[PDB]
Image: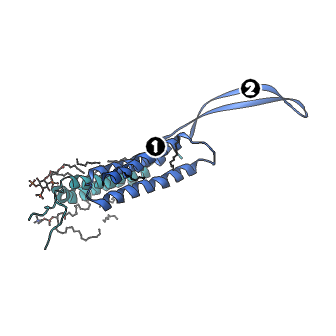
Chain colours: A cyan, B blue
Amino acid sequence: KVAYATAMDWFIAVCYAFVFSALIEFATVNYFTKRGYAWDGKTFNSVSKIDRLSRIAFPLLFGIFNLVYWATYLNRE
Amino acid sequence: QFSFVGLRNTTEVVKTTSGDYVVMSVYFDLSRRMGYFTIQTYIPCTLIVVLSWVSFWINKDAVPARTSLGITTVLTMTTLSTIARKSLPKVSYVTAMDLFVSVCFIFVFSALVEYGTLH
Ligand SMILES: CCCCCCCC/C=C/CCCCCCCC(=O)O[C@@H](COC(=O)CCCCCCCCCCCCCCC)COP(=O)([O-])OCC[N+](C)(C)C
Ligand SMILES: CCCCCCCC(=O)OC[C@H](COP(=O)(O)O[C@@H]1[C@H](O)[C@H](O)[C@@H](OP(=O)(O)O)[C@H](OP(=O)(O)O)[C@H]1O)OC(=O)CCCCCCC
Ligand SMILES: CCCCCCCCCCCC
Ligand SMILES: CCCCCCCCCCCC
Ligand SMILES: CCCCCCCCCCCC
Ligand SMILES: CCCCCCCC
Ligand SMILES: CCCCCCCC
Ligand SMILES: CCCCCCCC
Ligand SMILES: CCCCCCCC
């Protein structure tokens, strides 16, 4: 036990935000999901801009976090 | 876990079957820190409770989704209570940590029961 947060905790914490934010992202997509049925090979729910944008932002932003995190700690004296 | 607040000494005569003995005792005052338990216990307990709330924003028609979130949310609450309760010894009284998890248990259980009546 220690009364401070280690470098392990911050990566676990930020990873917690990314996984938790993924749940919130789907919940937001679910809010605007008007139709219950899916595409058949009448109107069908177009793929949400949230997903079509979250496909890019989440991995791209997570990658930037790794650069900052690993560069900060690996190069420390 | 603790911080050494201060020390205090005494001197008193304890009576026993073999005679009266002078006893000297040093009192060390130790104050707990909850920083670890927040990340260890409360923050997981707080965050899991939020997972129950997002059930409401999820559509009611998604019966497996709501139950999936509800049963997963309450059941992992049981594991958190036990592992959180594991850190304590075997003492027969509810503690403040026990009180927090139990109330969090009510919210997750009520959230599942909320959908049960909703359907
Ligand atoms: C995991 C192990 C398994 C590997 C899997 C193997 C596959 C390898 C992965 C191949 C890429 C996956 C796309 C292939 C399909 C092409 C179409 C597509 O979906 O692209 C979409 C773009 O969105 C993306 O493709 C983003 C993919 C993640 C990379 C994020 C960027 C950061 C790099 C990460 C590194 C960290 C960053 C570090 C910082 C530098 C476009 O969507 P669309 O619907 O096609 O659009 C319609 C047509 N249009 C495009 C003309 C408009
Ligand atoms: C992590 C959460 C972040 C908070 C984001 C929360 C912000 C937020 O809630 O945005 C969603 C909103 C609507 O997008 P979204 O796709 O989800 O919803 C569509 C929208 O309602 C259209 O207007 C609908 O068509 P219509 O006209 O009614 O006929 C369409 O239905 P359909 O045509 O298929 O039938 C719906 O699908 O805005 C954006 O488009 C870009 C958001 C960029 C989000 C990028 C942010 C990462
Ligand atoms: C169990 C360790 C959790 C550390 C704190 C996480 C805080 C971020 C989660 C919510 C982001 C939207
Ligand atoms: C796309 C939203 C991601 C939410 C979690 C991000 C928190 C850490 C910021 C990254 C620092 C570069
Ligand atoms: C694992 C804990 C289950 C919930 C306990 C219910 C009993 C009441 C606890 C609070 C009494 C003040
Ligand atoms: C936890 C609920 C997140 C918001 C879902 C609805 C979109 C504003
Ligand atoms: C997804 C591949 C990442 C590799 C980074 C380079 C160091 C292992
Ligand atoms: C894809 C980015 C990985 C970064 C690894 C650490 C570089 C110092
Ligand atoms: C009797 C246990 C609760 C079951 C749900 C009841 C909803 C009216």
Left or right placement of residue B66 versus residue B8 in this view: left
Residue in view at x 18 percent, y 65 percent:
A37
**Residue A71 seen in the figure:** no
- Up-down: is B44 above or below B14? below
- Return the residue nearer the eye: A67 or B18: B18
Instruction: Please state the horizontal and vertical placement of residue B52, each as a whole percent of the image.
Output: 36, 50
Amino acid type at image mark 2: Thr
Does mark 2 have its CB less than 8 Å from ligand 5?
no
User: Residue at position x 42%, y 54% from top?
Assistant: B74
Residue A61, how many percent across, how many down? 25, 54
Against B18, is A45 above or below?
below
Image quarter for ligand 7 equals: bottom left
Q: Is residue A45 above or below residue A69?
A: below
Query: Within 10 angstroms of label 2, few (less than 14), some, or many (20 or more) residues?
Result: few
Observer-nearest of A16 and B48 = B48
Read off the residue under disc 1: B103
State the image quarter where residue B6 is shown.
top right
Residue at mark 1 to residue at mark 2: CA–CA distance = 42 Å
Q: Secondary structure at mark 1?
A: helix
Q: Which residue is mark 2?
A: B10
CB at mark 1 closer than 8 A to ligand 5?
A: yes
> Do the residues at pointers 1 and 2 share their chain?
yes
Residue type at tag 1: Val
